[PDB]
Image (spheres, helix red, strand yellow):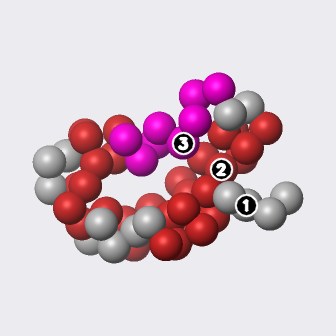
Amino acid sequence: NPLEFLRDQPQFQNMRQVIQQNPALLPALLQQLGQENPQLLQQISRHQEQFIQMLNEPP
């Protein structure tokens, strides 16, 4: 799945940041990921726990 790198790369963290302080655009990054490629979303399914886990970065 293309998420492996997504979860590893700042993609997950980075997002949390922008959306963390500036929660205006929200973590849409995911919407564009699953939407972009009709196959991505499916593979992304493995996320949720990890993806969202960071989406709520403590700091």
Q: Image quadrant of residue 4? A: bottom left
Question: Mark 2 and 1 residues: CB-CB less than 8 Å, in contact?
Answer: yes
- Viewer-nearest residue: 54 or 10: 54
Which residue sits at x=61%, y=57%? 55
Left of 54 or right of it: where is 46?
Answer: left
**Label 1: element kind:** loop
Q: Earlier in the sequence, mark 3 or mark 2?
A: 2
Label 1: few (<14), some (14–19) or many (≥20) C-alpha neighbours in 10 Å: few
Which residue sits at x=80%, y=63%? 58
Question: Mark 3 and 2 residues: CB-CB less than 8 Å, in contact?
Answer: yes
Q: Residue furthest right?
A: 59
Query: Which residue type carries mark 3?
Result: Pro
Label 3: few (<14), some (14–19) or many (≥20) C-alpha neighbours in 10 Å: some
Which residue sits at x=20%, y=61%? 42
Q: Earlier in the sequence, mark 1 or mark 3?
A: 3
Q: From which residue to which does the magenta span run?
A: 24-31
**From the viewer's perspective, is residue 25 above or below residue 35?**
above
> Magenta stretch: residue 6 in it?
no
- Viewer-nearest residue: 11 or 23: 23
Query: Which residue type carries mark 2?
Result: Arg
Q: Which residue is mark 3?
A: 27
Q: Which residue is mark 1?
A: 57
Q: Which residue is mark 2?
A: 16
